[PDB]
């Protein structure tokens, strides 16, 4: 009889929680290509000429 | 007797004495196997890449110079006759 509706209100309260989510990310660097160049005095000059 | 004549010389070798000795043989074997300078560079890289893995860069010629960033204790600079075999691994 002492515990009333206007002597003990009863509130509900929660916090806003973001939904958990599981994702994959694979980072692969730019491809690396072998190059073979030869330089001789003539091949320089041939272009130069 | 040509292997005794070439007598490959090592100016700068920032590498262990065991791995150095291996390079001398490969360096000699490369030249007597190969018909041109472009083939020498190709044979050295491919042989080392198989033995020790990673990203080698090999350069050889008459007259050049070389400032480079390399994996510490993976750089040798040997000249034989007039050919400087320069190989270096990078990360």
Image (cartoon, rainbow, N blue to C red):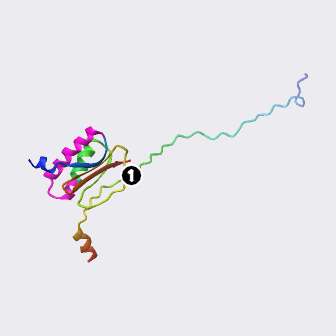
Going 26% across and 45% down the picture, which residue do you hit? B48
Horizontal and vertical percent for residue B85? Answer: 25, 52
Asked if the magenta segment contains residue A47, the reply would be no
Q: Outermost residue toward the top?
A: A1
B52 left or right, relative to B7: right
| Quadrant of residue B24 within the rendered picture | top left
A25 left or right, relative to B31: right
Going 26% across and 40% down the picture, which residue do you hit? B19
Q: Outermost residue toward the bottom?
A: A49
Residue that numbered label 1 is attached to: B69
Q: Name the secondary structure under disc 1.
A: loop
| Quadrant of residue B35 within the rendered picture | bottom left
Horizontal and vertical percent for residue B1? Answer: 8, 47
**What residue span does the magenta drawing correspond to?**
B16-40
Going 25% across and 73% down the picture, which residue do you hit? A45
Seen from the viewer's position, the closer of residues B59 and B5 is: B5
Seen from the viewer's position, the closer of residues B19 and A43 is: B19
What is the chain letter for disc 1? B
Seen from the viewer's position, the closer of residues A5 and B79 is: B79
| Quadrant of residue A8 within the rendered picture | top right
Horizontal and vertical percent for residue B42? Answer: 23, 53
A48 left or right, relative to B1: right
SS majority, magenta: helix
Horizontal and vertical percent for residue B72? Answer: 37, 44
């Amino acid at each position: 009889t002492l515990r009333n509706k206007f002597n003990y209100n009863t509130r509900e309260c929660q916090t806003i929680n973001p939904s958990i989510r599981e994702r994959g990310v694979s980072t692969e660097p730019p491809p690396s290509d072998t190059i073979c160049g030869n330089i001789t005095q003539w091949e320089i000059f041939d272009a130069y000429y | 007797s040509h292997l005794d004549k070439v007598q490959p010389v090592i100016k700068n070798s920032d590498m262990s004495v065991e791995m150095q000795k291996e390079v001398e043989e490969v360096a000699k074997k490369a030249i007597d196997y190969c018909n041109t300078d472009k083939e020498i560079a190709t044979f050295i890289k491919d042989d080392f890449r198989s033995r020790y893995h990673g990203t080698w860069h090999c350069i050889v010629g008459r007259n050049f110079g070389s400032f480079v960033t390399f994996e510490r204790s993976y750089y040798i600079y040997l000249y034989v006759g007039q050919l400087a075999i320069l190989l270096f691994k990078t990360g």
